[PDB]
Image (cartoon, rainbow, N blue to C red):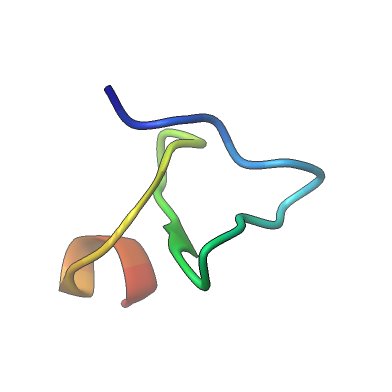
Length: 30
């Protein structure tokens, strides 16, 4: 699915979304 960030930190060098879900893109890293 996606995955929730941990203490404001995500693994796999991914980025935390505004919804608390990890992922990629400018909407996640921006």
